[PDB]
Length: 433
Ligand SMILES: [Zn+2]
Image (cartoon, rainbow, N blue to C red; front, side, top):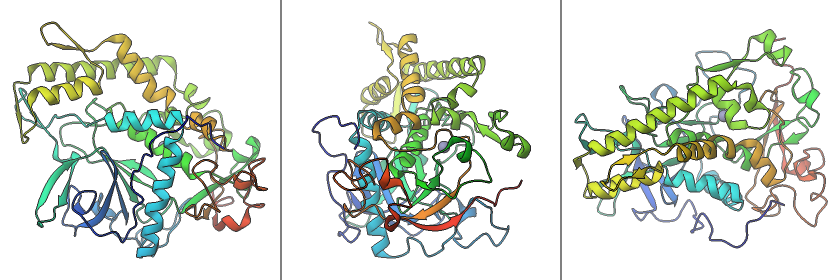
């Protein structure tokens, strides 16, 4: 089982059922920004600042509202399509309970407690004003919630977990942009939408030589979905603090002849998020440039707060919100009330978000088997069901104590634990080589 942290309150106070009656507070019909023009969807607030929408994501991107295999292109090797997935109440109930269970698995570790805490504290900055002396929310960092009287109220939030779009296995952490600001890269942060499903997982190979070869292996071991969700939450952490690395900054893979012969380039953001040996492929000089860059951005935020004389679109006070961001960014405060970025403190925060919160570290806490590198090749996708405790638990994942599955990651062994996995598609021998 996982490395415990002791008794603690659950991350999700209520055990929601999809059919629970709306109440206009934490079970509600809502609309996402853009909302162009969507029907409200039933959503669930599982924790302060965090909502779950048990629907296929046909909302965050207008060009991605069709769940049929793209009639436009031909299907990519590593993709999976099923337009019917997550269309029924039963599936949505299971989705909710699965996502809930994964949050609790994550929160049961000290590392996950730390990451989820950072995420909740990571309110997207109030940088919406055209007047540089007035604080104003950015409304794409909100959702609209239908209240008991049928009216909408605007609510700020940090994170939404939503079902995948057409390609079921294209999990990703995404967010609404601004035509002037790069919110995920300028220190501000923005509300994060993670496309994720707890109802599928990926197979990988236990031998590094096989896992990193595109032609070998059927995907004998299954990735623990808690690791997959944590990976996306790590991205969400970077993005909420506005320190994500521009996707265009890539490492030309030159440590894997197979990547090389395909000219595969992997984002630094990805290597950072994986951690371990991968993070070293970001060279000292370039990483140092990033840190300076983000340090400067934080200073600009401190400077904006200082100039702030008024606040608009809220009842909350100018003083209260100034302090919320002093707290998010760990700013220092003068005898005269001026805000400053402290260099030790910036380094500490930046490092916590980028070095401490990594996939490789979560693997250590969960004590599961996992890919050893991001620079591998996907083997297969399986259908799973982690909701029944007989299948998967908060403490043990698939590797259930006091059963044959406890030892040697037998629970993740899709051959031994075959009843828990239905292989839907092989990817090996689909790549271009
Ligand atoms: Zn990633």
